[PDB]
Image 1 (cartoon, rainbow, N blue to C red):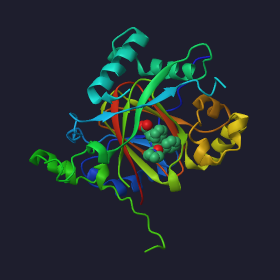
Image 2 (image 1 turned 90 degrees about the horizontal axis):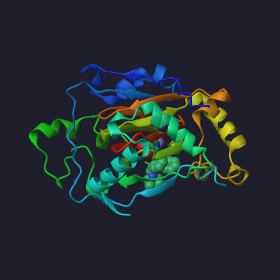
Image 3 (image 1 turned 90 degrees about the vertical axis):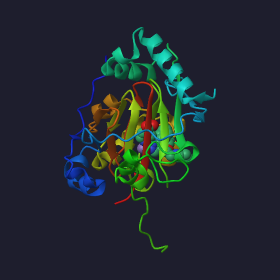
Length: 294
Ligand SMILES: O=C(O)c1ccnc(-n2ncc([C@H](OCCN3CCCCC3)c3ccccc3)c2-c2ccccc2)c1
Ligand SMILES: [Mn+2]
């Protein structure tokens, strides 16, 4: 029948005192958040970083995504991609883009993923390096001067360019950008080296997430292998993770705990070590993400 939304993941609204530095805050919420895999963090109301990408020269060629590709077995500016994205969604649902309920897009997305009668194809501006046109956060680069009202965000610990990224090893990365449209998605995966990830939605329509706690990681991998196509079941995890598309209800039917959330503009999503996650975009939006170490 229809998609059954998983339970909501934890949402934290830290005070200005708790918001002082992310690593200590993430360490404190860990007893709860590591049991849900993902969590959402809403900064205080007055914490509003300005968007710092060079919008004039921002150009990219998004990847083509066919939603039902497993069942079946153009260069844009930010403005032109947004026009394409809004036109697609308003045409698909026959209503203004901001009036489409998040539950309907979610229900339609998972129906289209398993549909053999309807081939829906979207585009995703994914894995755009922040080195190309700058980070969405203000940065003391020198490649783009910052206003005085911007400096606190250039120095903030929640600025994804200021997250610790070095892992201590016996030898003695930068954020990535995602320009989304309706139904553009990221399949089930964990980060390299089981690292944390922090994700910030700069603006636009919500990004819908699904997360699995790390204690159920082997359960998910067993379900994924049992139900993956026979040609992909034997592939190494790093390659299989390119096509690990699975309805959350299938995992839940196999006893795997799954949590969801709608990440709205200005909110963070943190994924914990070895927490499998997947999701899709409700519409035209802009996200920034990085892996970090504790
Ligand atoms: O869309 C998002 O909002 C999102 C949300 C959560 N997580 C990710 N992550 N997180 C790590 C990766 C990862 O790529 C990121 C770095 N990327 C690696 C190759 C060279 C270029 C840079 C990835 C990609 C495919 C499968 C599994 C993980 C990805 C990713 C990237 C592109 C498509 C699908 C997933 C994205
Ligand atoms: Mn990820």
